[PDB]
Length: 218
Ligand SMILES: [Cl-]
Ligand SMILES: [Cl-]
Image (cartoon, rainbow, N blue to C red; front, side, top):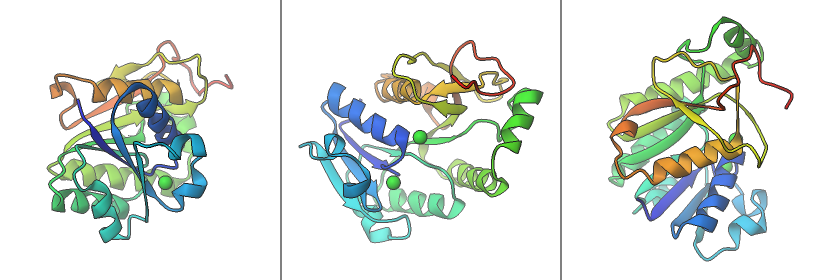
C-alpha cells in the first residue's frame, strides 16, 4: 500500500488512465510531472483535490526532484531514453525514493516468438527500440526497488480488463493488451501486500489468448 505517488510522463495514455483510476478507487495523493500538463491533460483528471501538478522536463533536475520529494512510489510512464532515465534515477536517489514502477516494451530480450518478433521490429523505428533498451539498462543498473512492465502492443477497450503477467525469461506469446488491462495490472501491483514478486523484476503484461503473429485490428 502507498499513499503518495508521483507519475512521471503524466500526459501518456496509460498514465492518464492510471491517474483517473487512482482518483476514483483510492485515497492516494497524486503528483503529476511533465511539460505543459495543465493543457495536455483534461480537466476531469486535473482539477481534483488530490492532484498536484508540477510542470517540467527530465532535464530540469530541480523541478524533477520537487515532484518526487516525499513520494512513496514513482510511476514512469515512458522509458524511452537512457539520458532521461539516468536523470530520473539520480533525482530518486537524491530524495531517498526507492520504489519505482516503469513501463517498457515487450520484445527487447527476444521473448517474442519468431513471427511476432519480426512484425514488431519492422513496425518500430530503430531509434525508438534503442532508446527503450538504454532506458531499461539504466534502470536495471540502479539500486532501486523497481518493477519494469514489459507491455505488448497496446489498444483501447474499456470492456477488456483481463491481463496475465509473464515472468522474465518466459516466452511471451500475447500479441496485444488493452491500456485498461495494463492499468488494472498497475493498480493490482500497487495493492500487493507482498512486494517480493515485483522486487527488481521485469514482468510482461499481455491479454490472455492473443497468441497471434501480429496485434489484431480489434
Ligand atoms: Cl508527460
Ligand atoms: Cl500509453
